[PDB]
Length: 48
Length: 48
Image 1 (cartoon, rainbow over the protein chains, first blue to last red):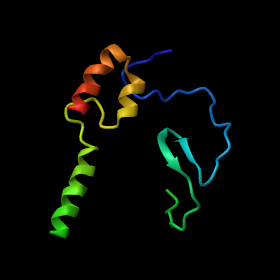
Image 2: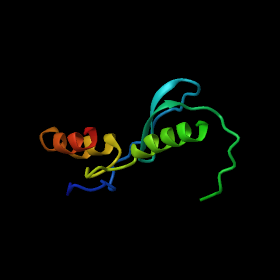
Image 3: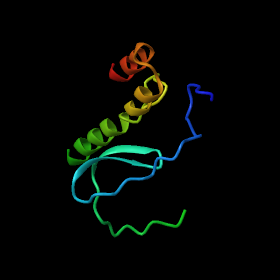
């Protein structure tokens, strides 16, 4: 098990969480970590 | 004057994404991937 100074991309399962809306929370979306409120949006994201 | 104030604010926000010689611009990544005895110098580079 190698840990360099680099992104750790071999992961044990960690996806069992429930999203909460309109509340200031610490979120981790597939490696993107941030703090804020999550709201429904009308942004038309492209599929990729 | 409105444009100059907006441009200064935009540049100041843009400078958050500048490494300033640190391993990464985002503080969370450098704190998470590096131990505090070594991460302190990178955090100092970002702080300064």
